[PDB]
Amino acid sequence: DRIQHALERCLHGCWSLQELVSRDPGHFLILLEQILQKTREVQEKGTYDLLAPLALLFYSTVLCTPHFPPDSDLLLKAARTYHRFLTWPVPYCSICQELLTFIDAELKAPGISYQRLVRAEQGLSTRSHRSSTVTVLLLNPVEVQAEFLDVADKLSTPGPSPHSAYITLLLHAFQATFGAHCDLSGLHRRLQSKTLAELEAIFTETAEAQELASGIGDAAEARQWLRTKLQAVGEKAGFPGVLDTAKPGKLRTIPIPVARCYTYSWNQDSFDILQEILLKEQESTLRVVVFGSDRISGKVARAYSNLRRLENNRPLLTRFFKLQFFYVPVDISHYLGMLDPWYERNVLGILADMLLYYCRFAARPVLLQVYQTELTFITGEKTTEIFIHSLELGHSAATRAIKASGPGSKRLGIDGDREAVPLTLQIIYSKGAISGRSRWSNMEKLCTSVNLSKACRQQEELDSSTEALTLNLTEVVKRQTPKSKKGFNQISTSQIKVDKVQIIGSNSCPFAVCLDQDERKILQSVIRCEVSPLLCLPIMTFSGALP
Amino acid sequence: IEFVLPSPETALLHVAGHGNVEQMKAQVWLRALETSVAADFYHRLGPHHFLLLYQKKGQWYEIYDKYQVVQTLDCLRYWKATHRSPGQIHLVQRHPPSEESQAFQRQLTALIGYDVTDVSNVHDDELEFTRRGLVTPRMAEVASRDPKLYAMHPWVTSKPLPEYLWKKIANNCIFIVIHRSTTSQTIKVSPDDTPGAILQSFFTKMEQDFVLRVCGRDEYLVGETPIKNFQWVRHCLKNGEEIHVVLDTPPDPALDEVRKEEWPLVDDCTGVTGYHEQLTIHGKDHESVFTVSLWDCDRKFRVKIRGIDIPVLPRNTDLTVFVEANIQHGQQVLCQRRTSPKPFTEEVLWNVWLEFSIKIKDLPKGALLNLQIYCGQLLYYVNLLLIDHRFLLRRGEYVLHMWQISFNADKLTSATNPDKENSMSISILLDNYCHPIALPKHQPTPDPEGDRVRAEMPNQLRKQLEAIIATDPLNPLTAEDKELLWHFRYESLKHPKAYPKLFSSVKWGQQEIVAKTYQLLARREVWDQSALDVGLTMQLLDCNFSDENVRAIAVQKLESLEDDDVLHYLLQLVQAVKFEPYHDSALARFLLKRGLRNKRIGHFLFWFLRSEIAQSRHYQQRFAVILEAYLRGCGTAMLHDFTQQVQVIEMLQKVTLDIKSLSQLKQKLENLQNSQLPESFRVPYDPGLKAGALAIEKCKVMASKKKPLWLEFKCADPTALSNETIGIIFKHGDDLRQDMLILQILRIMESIWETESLDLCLLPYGCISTGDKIGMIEIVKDATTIAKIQQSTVGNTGAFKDEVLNHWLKEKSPTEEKFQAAVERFVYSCAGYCVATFVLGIGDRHNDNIMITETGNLFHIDFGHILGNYKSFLGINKERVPFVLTPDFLFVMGTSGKKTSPHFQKFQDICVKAYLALRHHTNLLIILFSMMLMTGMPQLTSKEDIEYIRDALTVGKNEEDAKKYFLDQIEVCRDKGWTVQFNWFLHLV
């Protein structure tokens, strides 16, 4: 009853408390009952919002639960309930099909999914063709946060040995089929004396049996064959009685071990250390966890753009591999939480558990909308490929700053809030790309300051999922020459919804760009600025961009 | 399924079930590449795709659908019926169309005036699939066609000869004047003798391979039918003219050859959808689910309005805008949702999910999502067919270009505005699915019969139902009436007159009610042996019935019409094609088949359909596809005739356009006559007549604000008995679709009066619309205008005198007997036109649009001029008269004493007879009026306009009361003698 209340409190948002209430093996089955009831209500009432969090909670609980009872019908009821979801739209029926396959695999092989996840994360020996492993990198500058640095240190500890990982995997696999009829204490005592090679052989045999049983085709026959094979393996390896040996021996949770997380600071050098950790792994998939505020959003987008330019002839992706990116805020997180309520409640909101949960159970990538900026200089050289979230354009003190920077130094004074002398500004904006009809419009006047903002920064009070850009004319000319009425003098905040922008200066009036107060980039002396809108940065979230 | 590769290589494939096996193209392609290095080499030179073909009946068929093998069930069914388990499918190359094929397509495009092959304004392949699917009825009609009878196209009727024509047969004998070379012989033959008997009698009255062709016309008196049953013979008897024929060699059937079909037969699109049990996901293993039944989806319907995009804002109204989405089925809004009002600018963003209260399983076939942009009133509209023509629910993003308004047929179109660069555009998102969602087959079988009722109705409820059935079509049904009709649906089948009301009582927004309706109409028999009622069929083909099965029922009853009966209602059927939700409907197939069967029906169908292609953008593509199918069907001789007609029409279009921009007309006419003028062309409003040279010295331009061309052509037939020319008015700047609809209604009314043995001397002229605001009108000879008759003596200053018309008619009568005949004809024609214009509501006209011949007959002309004014104003803000009964007409009839006269009494009697005759067909007249208002009006109609007729036709009243009503109308006409005409003159001046 209290588990149902905790579930209800979790949905209408609590989270770690809800996960920790499941301390007893029967709490797993109780929570599964509650989740199935909530899912049935959701389907009956057609509530699209609650499907993804409920699906994820069911997946996690079934992954962690030990030894579904032989008489239990949770798996069959869940299979029917989800198979009823095939008439739902694509982002929901996709999760439906994923859970249906997962449920079928867990019903045929009771501990297939937990064994798969733990074996992949710990990088244990695999006899399957093209063996896979999971590596976690926590990219933490030493100036991110003390609490987050400490939690990364806790995750960075090597912790369990391959011996202990094999013991835990074998214990979970044998309990998932022999729940209360196996002596887990005696089995662990016998396993503690086993050698590493023996443990590896036993684990490989059990894993092969589970994979074979996962595709038998008949649930009862698959379970019977897996039970027979596990009994044979136990008899071969000298295991004690595992068939109805002792009723007193009750269930044990066997929680997921801490994944082998590596904490290395890359110092914002465009993801250089990823190649180093590839090389170390040589001597599959890797999970990148990015910690930091908005100040490193530019660094992250440059790094990913460089990686997406380079991987075509780099060993990171040519070797069997999968690169996943996770972001923790410590405003990308605002946008992600706006799209994903689960991300808002769990990540954007004892902490190592949540980081591991986000790493393990976030499988839907959301492509962050980034803007491609190209600047044509006053000297004839053309620069391209600049990525931002907002932009401040036209400042003459900023072009003095860019001239001070030159071709090999930082643009000191590009931070904005600087007086600008009037310049000859041409504004070109493209409108109407919602219907595929791009309409270009032109103005040519005198201007000092222009704001180029993304609605996603303030999308909480606007049209849902609006990828458009806002061009704002405000605080213009009055900063230096308030009496210059010929140009854009004063001008209250005027907003134009735009998608592509071209702002053109003049040689006698040099132009400048402020890239969210990023002074690291070098741009010599620019005049023409072109901003254009699948793009970049697929940050993983629990549920993708629901339509 | 064995496959035959393009090298005679036989690759034995295996039946791969039905789940996502339209990679069968890719599967067989990869298998061919593996099994032949020649295929590997040809991969670098082969086309993009190939074609899979089989042989259903020896003739070659194509599998034209790329989604699932469930579609291909017809080939498998034929193979299992023939018991040949290994089926052969030939893989053939996508050979490009030949040079002659492209030339023929270009000629067809020139004839149609629209490029059917252009796929730049389609978001699906419904039009192309209709093009492919219309081949089967076309080939069926071409194969089952009598060559000689088609070539000679006799115009016959099976209706009994009217008594006023029977009295014109003096001694049960008819004289026919047969011409051979310059010799002419009169042969007396009984009216019950076939043309073969007449020809044998002529030969015995001294080879035998000859026919009788009407002199001066391309009309033949052939076939096995009594000589009295020919429309030409009846026309000659009615006009008292002598029947002249010539002994002509029969036209060669080889001239009507049809070129071979390029495309293989496409079969049907009903394969993708099966019964519910086959499409449902319940009982499946979530791995064999390749399609999802529509009736499984229990969720509410949901559509995401993304935004609105316009290049430049209209300045009519602004400052607020919202979107209203209506799920509706045949003008019945099943559900309606609205968006929040937002400021009206060039681009408005909502990105809001509108979720209706209608379940997805409850969406019927032909359900229509009407997206309307309102302001603050309505600004734009567009429609999307929720269920595709393959019985598939729509999914994905749609950028639909909207229609701008300037109850209407054009509001039901599923076409998208072709003006991409300037029109309003609305972006919507419909949910995507892993598996396609298919609406199951309409009804598996009524084996349980839907619990057909056994208990007798109580007497009181029987009386209530019978009272409901007898009521007029326009009388609304309350909730109680609909509940009674549906609750006793199995009793309402026994009365065919209740079918429109019964099917209007069906709740189309519920799936089970639609299934019960299909079970109900699956056991229709009283309707099948029911005598054909044109009014009931028209009611079933109206805009209120969007269901495919009801339309199929109506067309099935239409199929029993005669050729002349189809000619009577051909324009109404073409207009009713607008109401069909899908392009390939039973009405389109019926029109195609009956235009291919008869040459006259085909000619008039071509012109009626080309006019709609030219003037109506909403239904350009559907009508263009239908016309392309017909033109591919008809023979090459009639294609050449159509080409010559289109050539002369286009060059006269150019001449009218050049003259209207401004002796000059004369010079342009000699430029035409010496170059680019065909030697002879078939007259568009009269296919039996061939106009030859142009009498340039007689052509002119009327003193009209439109400046039409008065042309007179020479008759191309040397066998013509008179030197009379052919008059044709080519007019620009007026919409002639309304005029020709009114003329068709007048012809139908005349047919009704003939059925009740009444000759009102009302004869409509020949008007055909040929293009956007341009058309052609027949010139009635020896006729002038009443306004011009008045202006001869008094009327230039507005003064009007009563004796003008009687004296004018007297002057044109050579003798006293001719004057008496002219007076009688004037009385009859005036009564007929007064009754017709009062019933149709176009009676409030002026003298400038009323004509009279020298024989006394009366005419109303330029119906488009007054129809629009009547629709806009209805005469409620001025002094309105029921019809033009001017005191000059009364003086021609009576003694002007305003008491009575024998001719006036006869006029009253005959007009009352005609009024009651029309009241006998009240239902047909009402449905025709409703269709005319829906289709012929570029504006938007509503109630209080359609129902006017049920006040004019005196619906629901005694015959004596209706007679008194028409007498009161006559009296109020006699009260306003010159007031309304003087007011019209002041308004014009």
Image (cartoon, rainbow, N blue to C red):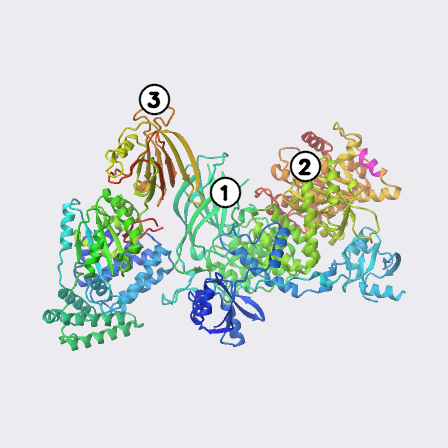
Q: Residue at x 13, y 49 (%)?
A: A150
As helix, strand or loop, the secondary structure at mark 2 comes to: helix
Q: Chain of mark 1?
A: B
Which region shows up in magenta?
B803-810
Judging by the rendered image, the residue that carries numbered circle 1 is B421
Query: Mark 1 and mark 2: span between their CA atoms?
Result: 30 Å
Residue B79 placement, left or right of A527: right
Q: Amino acid at mark 3?
A: Lys
1 and 2 marks on the same chain: yes
Residue A55 placement, left or right of B424: left
2 and 3 marks on the same chain: no
Q: Amino acid at mark 2?
A: Lys
Query: Mark 1 and mark 3: span between their CA atoms?
Result: 42 Å
Please tell me which residue lies in front, A421 or B20. Answer: A421
Pinpoint residue B634: horizontal percent, then vertical percent: 66, 59
Circle 3 packing at 10 Å, graded few (<14), some (14-19), many (20+), is: few
Judging by the rendered image, the residue that carries numbered circle 3 is A483
Q: Earlier in the sequence, mark 1 or mark 2?
A: 1
Mark 1–mark 2 CB contact (< 8 Å): no
Q: Amino acid at mark 1?
A: Glu
As helix, strand or loop, the secondary structure at mark 1 comes to: loop
Question: Which residue is most to the right?
Answer: B206
Q: Residue at x 60, y 38 (%)?
A: B872
As helix, strand or loop, the secondary structure at mark 3 comes to: loop
In the displayed structure, would residue A517 be above or below residue B628?
above
Which secondary structure type mostly characterizes the magenta part of the structure? helix
Pinpoint residue B760: horizontal percent, then vertical percent: 76, 47
Q: Which mark is residue B297?
A: none
User: Residue B896: in sight, yes or no?
Assistant: no
The image quarter in which residue A77 lies: bottom left
Residue B395 placement, left or right of A77: right
Judging by the rendered image, the residue that carries numbered circle 2 is B660
